[PDB]
Image (cartoon, protein in one colour):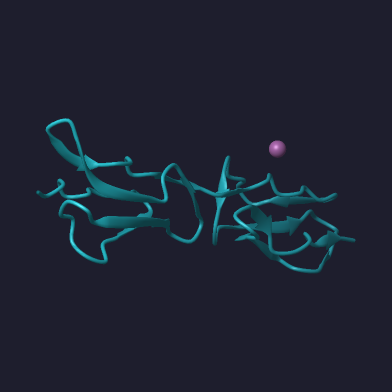
Length: 124
Ligand code: NI
């Protein structure tokens, strides 16, 4: 008469509008910076002698920005293998060059895809 407690989605959320008894529905979504892979909702049904969820919980995978751009006569202060939402890259110009433009850029999300907030600075 009742399905088992839904469980948890890492970096995701489970919405339960009206309990988890036979005939109930639950919905899923991912936290900002993550993409949902799998089911978007699940229904409590009967299969054989089991009262179970129609669909398994989805996964919420981190959205990554592409590798940041390098700049001539400058360096990135410790590049990460992966950049996710809200993470940033800070540049520094080499000896003899002055920086022009944004000092740091951030990994943002544009339609479920990682996108850098702006252009890198220039070292003149
Ligand atoms: Ni690449």
